[PDB]
Image (tube, grey):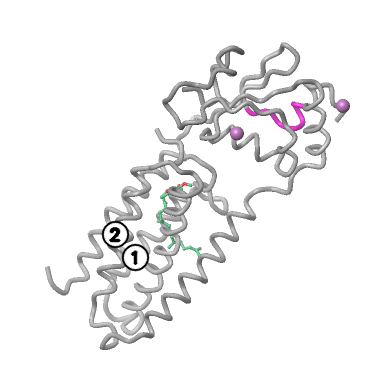
Amino acid sequence: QRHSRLILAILAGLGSLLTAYLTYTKLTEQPAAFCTGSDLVLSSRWAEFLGIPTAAVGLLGFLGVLALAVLPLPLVKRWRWPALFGLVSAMTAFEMYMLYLMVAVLRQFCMYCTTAIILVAGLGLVTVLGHRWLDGGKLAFSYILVAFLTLVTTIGVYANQVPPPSPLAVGLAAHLRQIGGTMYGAYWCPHCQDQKELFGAAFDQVPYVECSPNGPGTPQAQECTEAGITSYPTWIINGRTYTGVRSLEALAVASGYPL
Ligand SMILES: [Hg+2]
Ligand SMILES: [Hg+2]
């Protein structure tokens, strides 16, 4: 109701728990190549960061705030209320990029993902509202520092996630072009993107049939059903149908390209 850091502690609970959940989800997942048709944006790319699940990155942060909201008072007097600023600010930086992706690049809504953000959104709004240097503008800057320092790392670490496209990719793309080799799949599907990852620069050459232009759970485009496509990144290469992400390695086998 008024001036209370316990309100942080609570929101850190919910943050922690939800975050712990999706961690246990991605960790227990039974992996797949096709994605015929819990959530898709949730097990997109990005959801895995630096080794650990992004949920886990979320975890470290969320219980990291919980502890500081609760651990005080000797051992760390001066340091806890700003350390509690630096972590929440850094979470806000990360929230914004996730939110960005969600809205802008993935274009799909994820209700676990929105929750997490709303939670952090709140984690700031409360953390903002302490006595806070008789309201200094040192925040304004301090925030802009930490926010921006994070968005160079986060955006950095995500762009360094995708590996430099294989040497094979260039030829295998322009070959599949020749021998009619076609990839049927949905733009939304994490794996139709997974396959598109492996080719990279080269993918612009690869014969691609988009199957579901208008989102998930809406009629699959006509070209696809006529070729009997039932899952999402299937390959029709010379009468033979490969149902699932294949390596550049294995597509070169299936397509006659000498590896
Ligand atoms: Hg060829
Ligand atoms: Hg695709």
Which residues lie in the magenta part?
245-251
Give the image quarter of residue 72.
bottom left
Considering depth in this image, is 233 or 157 the residue closer to the camera?
Answer: 233
On screen, 216 above or below 132?
above
104 in relation to 148, above or below? above
Image coordinates of residue 259 in percent, x first then y, are 85, 30
Total marks drawn?
2
Q: Can you name the residue that lies furthest to the left here?
A: 1
Going by the numbered disc 1, the residue's amino acid type is: Val
Q: What label does residue 173 carry, if any?
A: none
State the SS at label 2.
helix
> Looking at the picture, which amino acid does disc 2 mark?
Ala
Among the 4 quarters of the image, the one containing residue 199:
top right
What residue lies at 47% left-to-right and 57% top-to-bottom? 97
| Disc number placed over residue 65 in the picture, else none | 1
As drawn, which residue projects farthest toward the front?
222
Q: Earlier in the sequence, mark 2 or mark 1?
A: 2
Disc 2 and disc 1 in contact, CB within 8 angstroms: yes
Using the image as rendered, state which of residue 106 and residue 36 is in the foreground: 106
Whether residue 100 sits left or right of residue 257 in the image: it is left
Neighbour class for label 2 at 10 Å: few (<14), some, many (≥20)? Answer: many
Residue 22 lies, in percent from the top left, at: 39, 43
Q: Which residue is mark 2?
A: 12
Along the horizontal axis of the image, is 4 left or right of 237?
Answer: left
Residue 179 pos. (x, y %):
80, 21
For the N terminus, which image quadrant?
A: bottom left
Q: What percent of the width, then of the height, locates residue 181?
A: 74, 22
